[PDB]
Image (cartoon, rainbow, N blue to C red; front, side, top):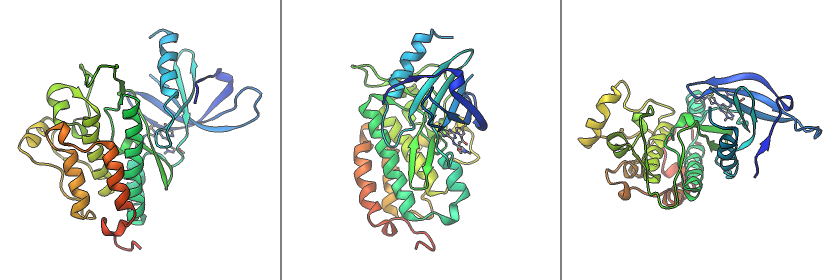
Length: 280
Ligand SMILES: *CCC(=O)N[C@@H]1CN(c2nc(Nc3cn(C)nc3OC)c3ncn(C)c3n2)C[C@H]1F
């Protein structure tokens, strides 16, 4: 996997897919000069650093090559930065589970848990802390295959850095580990906490965590030992994996490699672990 530098004439925006503080993402078409191959892509136009700085960050990003991380294919530098990425035709997993809640079986849910853990383990191998894992930031390539994506919060740790120490950026409190809320500290193990919340989202078919509760109250609820409730479809075995992800001691939490093993075992006999009517 290598970074391609695109000229504006190489790609076209077709329609908007979504928008946020990061910028806007479009469905588009990329035709590399004289290659005659038409590639469906997502184009993320970000809302300055030197061009070489941006290209360097894009090079590292483009080297992230794993079946369960959405890949940067190329970049175009003009008045704006435009990132050309793999298109995930089914959109964010949050909306997908909300839409198809009555037609999603245990096999798909547990498989997604495995896949997200595989992608996160790869990011950890690359020394990348994601810092924004949530169902909204997982994308659906096919119903059978999902990929993690990133909107600017991910950080590369230095050879001797064990944690990332954040500053004033806005934070997704309800997905964060307690140590991140209290001390602005982020690690692969705080990503594990977020992974647990992400799994809870999937198992509740996209429900809102700590629904209706002010973000300002969350740290106090967590300090009292309270956590997100057991989803209706979850046997206690699955809920206990979530609860392990939210233990106060970061080193008490499972690592992604362990999560891959545990969810993979469950995915072999999915109906023993999730209880879904009509499944199957
Ligand atoms: C739930 C989060 C959300 O809606 N985020 C938006 C969508 N984003 C995004 N979307 C796609 N693909 C997509 C979405 N829809 C409705 N249709 C499609 O494709 C036909 C995508 N592919 C790759 N990347 C990076 C994507 N991002 C991100 C936010 F804009």
